[PDB]
Image 1 (cartoon, each protein chain N blue to C red):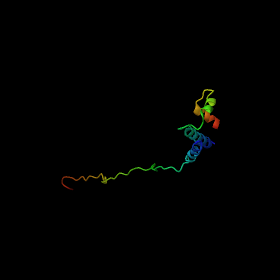
Image 2: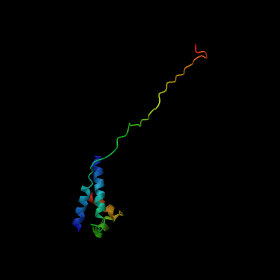
Image 3: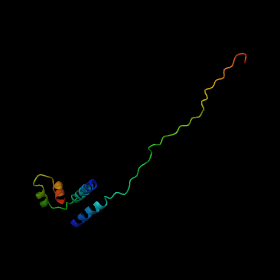
Length: 50
Length: 51
């Protein structure tokens, strides 16, 4: 349903924004792994959570 | 510290719930003007001698 997809997308962005604010929840070692392809740190963590 | 971040993220999701909507119902409504005089459109024609 379009409602479920919209709800999931908005909630996911709120989590990512809060997680990466101030001191990030995820260490720099995991960011290096998730940014090997070329995607940014925020984007790499976002796909893994999904 | 990392627990406060996880707990903060969950509270952000729970706070995203919508309460209600508010709007004005004005469609179909028009203002009213006031006409002060009644048009009669009458004239009295009388001869000079009054006959």
